[PDB]
Image 1 (cartoon, one colour):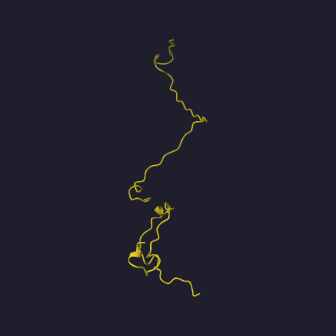
Image 2 (image 1 turned 90 degrees about the vertical axis):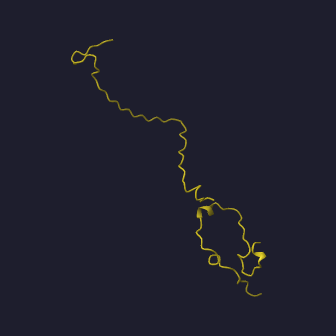
Image 3 (image 1 turned 180 degrees about the vertical axis):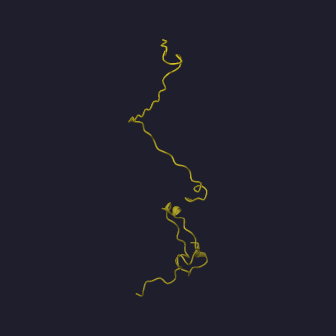
Length: 50
Length: 51
């Protein structure tokens, strides 16, 4: 449960410094429905469609 | 028969106001619009213009 780090100055310190890098591509059956659109102030203001 | 050609008819563009058309609105127009008298000839009585 307690393995000392004799060669290191601090035994209780976390000697390592890890950097992870993961990339995953996962085909899935989720719907991924549509992307809405913003509203134009000109429409409903100047009555382009009347 | 004589020649069947019109002589009394206002010019569609030059006899009316010069106004800017709204093309977007005209796209959403698929209904029968009225064609009132006074658009076919200038020999129209006062009352018949609105008909």
